[PDB]
Image 1: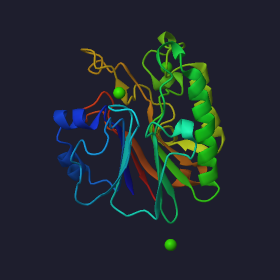
Image 2 (image 1 turned 135 degrees about the vertical axis):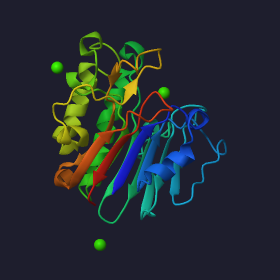
Image 3 (image 1 turned 180 degrees about the vertical axis):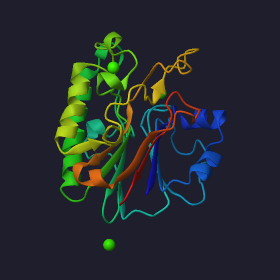
Length: 252
Ligand SMILES: [Ca+2]
Ligand SMILES: [Ca+2]
Ligand SMILES: [Ca+2]
C-alpha cells in the first residue's frame, strides 16, 4: 500500500498555492495524512471522490488540526488518546484496519527557547504509552510531523540548533525512546547514512533552494513491519507548504 504524510501549513493556504485535488489524483495513494490543517467545521470544501475523509479539529481556531484520507473504509476511527490535556488540539487520528493501525500525529512544538519542553516531554510519554497499547493488539504505522530531527544527519546545521526547538537533547532522546520501544524510522531503515534528506525548510528567500532543511516528518512502523517496507521517500519537488510530503510503500 502507498501512504503519504504532509504538514500543509494550513489547508486553506496549501489549496491557494497548489492544486491539492489534482495532487491527490496524480499520486493516487491508498492513505494520505495531513497535519496543521488549521480548520474547523465548515471552513473548506474537501470532499474528494475515492476517499473516506476523517478530520480532527483543535478547539482554538486557525491552529493545528489533522486529517486522514483513506480509499478503504477502516473498521474504526479514534480521535485523540483519551486524555483531556492531550486532546484539545486535533493532533492525533488512528484508523483501525483488519491487520494494522494507521495513525497520524502532529506533535506539539517545544516553542522558542524550549519554553514548552515540559509539556512536550509529557506528550511524548503519553503518546508512546498509547502507541504501545495499540501495538499489543496489531502492528502500527505512524506518520506525521514529529517536530524533531533525530540525529545530526537529520538537519543541515545541527551545531546551531542544540538549544532550539526540534533539536534539543530532550526531544532527540524522546524519539530514541520511541524507537527503542520496538519501532523503526522507515526512511532510515532504507537510507541509514544519507545526508541532506530533509522535509522542512524555512520559507526565507534561498533557504529551500540551498537545501537548508530538517527531516522532521516521518513514517514510524512497528519493528515487526520492518521487512514489509518496499520504499520510503521524501517528495522534495512538491511545493505548497514549508514542508514537503513524505511517503511509504509497505506490504500490509
Ligand atoms: Ca506551520
Ligand atoms: Ca483477513
Ligand atoms: Ca556528516
